[PDB]
Length: 320
Length: 13
Ligand SMILES: Nc1ncnc2c1ncn2[C@@H]1O[C@H](COP(=O)(O)OP(=O)(O)NP(=O)(O)O)[C@@H](O)[C@H]1O
Ligand SMILES: [Mg+2]
Image 1 (cartoon, each protein chain N blue to C red):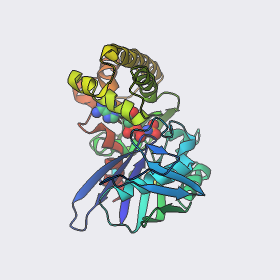
Image 2 (spheres, rainbow over the protein chains, first blue to last red; image 1 turned 180 degrees about the vertical axis):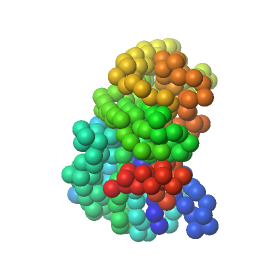
Image 3 (cartoon, each protein chain N blue to C red; image 1 turned 90 degrees about the vertical axis):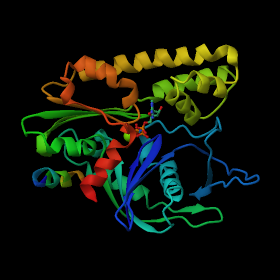
């Protein structure tokens, strides 16, 4: 079994092919607290131990570990998150080989050549031993690494002359990863990583607002509100203090404007790209402003209906 | 296809 694991700070995305050749996808939010959870009734809890420390998957706890940083790539929580994603995917527990991911600036030196040091640090992290309480964990056999952003442009780069270049803008929870890549993947003009520019800018602001509105929860719940920002009834069902909905929506709106302006300023630093692609969960939030800011003709702008999965799908199309 | 997929393999390390 070979499983493609785009292991992002916010969500693990999995893609893999079944025995009968059908392709499956699974997403798994990285919300874990440093304590075992308690099972009541029909609730199956996932309690893990790694290096003498206990964790549980907990989607609602305000004490869920905040994972919005570079260190997380090689962290213990990462290993828990990836095992948990495997254990909730529907695949039978087993040995597996995996292809995981690194941020551009971790995967590449300033010359756009692999940073074998960091690439190996990544592979070694998945050697850490982990226990699931009252159950068996998958065993992680062979580990290979790919860069983030770039693999998502695979299909599009195929029908692109080697003179055209595609700007792939990957906005995740922690990091803005930008790459400019020549047609047929014949070259890489430029990479760029900003690990202080993520949707967490918004997540963090929404989380604080929710707490003020007496809806104290995890980063995940805050993202859940960002995802449903356009649904006033959803907002009204989730947010406890009915009198403070505008505090959440406006806090969200201001951080979104900040997100936008910061992202657009970053684009000003690229030039000569003929095509523009926007991928990641953040794509939904910035795609209009990007298309507009780049004056790229409609046909040269690329945005899928499942932006969060663009990367892991590309990893699959390439490496499976 | 073949040229792109070829180059794609440098993305796997
Ligand atoms: N449909 C949606 N609409 C708006 N925002 C979304 C949507 N889906 C996901 N998001 C946001 O996008 C973020 C998750 O993006 P994702 O691309 O999965 O990050 P990641 O890859 O896990 N983190 P990173 O390590 O920075 O690449 C969350 O913070 C969500 O708030
Ligand atoms: Mg990502």
